[PDB]
Image (tube, rainbow over the protein chains, first blue to last red):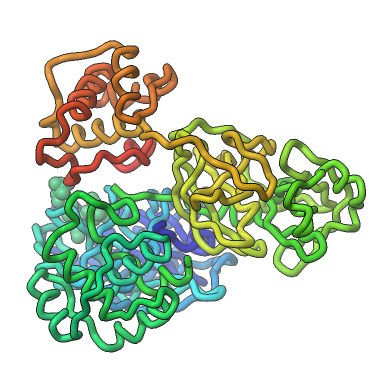
Length: 297
Length: 298
Ligand SMILES: *[C@H](O)[C@H](C[C@@H]1CCNC1=O)NC(=O)[C@H](CC(C)C)NC(=O)OC1CC2(CCN(C(=O)OC(C)(C)C)CC2)C1
């Protein structure tokens, strides 16, 4: 089961940011609201926005920030990469303990999808190897954030900016740097070739075993390098030794050597699933990390 | 299409732990009442075939430890309603949302906030199967975790977790303590009915496919509801109810495809199969998205 982190600590930070006829979401932490800088653009502006130029021509009072029914007065503004930072005259008493992190491709996070500053849904995503995310984001979702929670600490890793023509999504870290080769401009952008997150597929196969499901297992084995030759042929990421290490706990728990599960996955890549399904899926799933699997088994 | 859960914060603000002796589970604190599974009053050997009424007569208010985090909530009354305990406490929860208690129908989906020792671990979307089980992620200590939907700002609580079945699926009650399906809160081996496919949700999925321009499977014909139901059961599909036809109304209006015409298309898919084709990029028909879910994501 794909499980998201409880979203309450993040819900308490979501606000609405408006500039002109453009409205999206902001993240209110202490006395600063973070949001995508393209809020300052109009229709025309978005095709090729000179953001430093557009920003210098804005005043604080052109930014309407609403926390529910309350307006928050903007007393200062600055831009860090693709994120706008609006200083407000009120501190958010619901600010959690937090940090800003930049996540690695293959890592997972929860997304709190919001519209008009109001939380609407929560779901689990992975940072794809090509630095897209297979999100569910509609008009007005920009400024929705992604996060992980460790203890009481929220690690914010993603802020939402755009959708690509293939229907996947792109955004930045909370420092405003995009994941991937994308730009916050209204143009058709393609991503690099995506690949499948191999260490996560292996984790999920282990999960299917832990769940008493093992039709895909076999007696064969493989070396790491020979597995990786086949993996790359099928646009799977190569498996590193640290990935093998990371899979130990699941390996121990099932008594199945990592490289034995690699030999099972190799057979699936070459033969297909021949109708059969694994944990309900006709497709090999690659958006559970080993941690995700462990913490839920 | 993703399994998307509701934001969990309004429910997180209601979770507590309830302990009797060394047995700890979760409870739901709304206004000045805490709701939890009655089997908190059981020891190990009580769970085999508990006499709940005789177990409760021995208990007093001061035997219940209710905690929000580490802070004790004093219990000032107790009673049993079906399979839930209602513990009256001396503090009204200041985080109580607007809420309702609803009893859902099979096929309906809801979010579960999986909790341990009163602390949330994760949130996910569940569907009530036609055999009144859910495929959860519930570990020891998860009992009392709740399922819910959020409409406007109103939380509709529909599920409270009580047990696991020998096949690994899960069973529980509504917030009035009435089990979904033919299960009892005893630690005995109980079997669920053979499960079936949630027809109304498949139809919702086919409407979703049409909304996104994937409509090769629409045929020129229609059917009666009875004829469809008799065929559907031969494929281990749930028969449709009138309420099912009704909740497909909005998607039928959005697409202009009458419900019974879509039923005719599905019947053809069942009888002829997919013939190598895909719908929304899958050869499998999805049955855990409700008509409401589809609309929320389109
Ligand atoms: C901010 O809320 C918004 C979020 C977008 C809106 C729709 N889904 C989203 O994630 N972001 C923006 O509007 C971007 C602003 C720029 C200044 C960066 N622009 C875009 O995201 O580009 C448009 C979305 C787009 C529309 C058409 N098309 C499409 O229909 O795709 C399929 C897969 C549905 C056919 C591609 C995506 C271009």
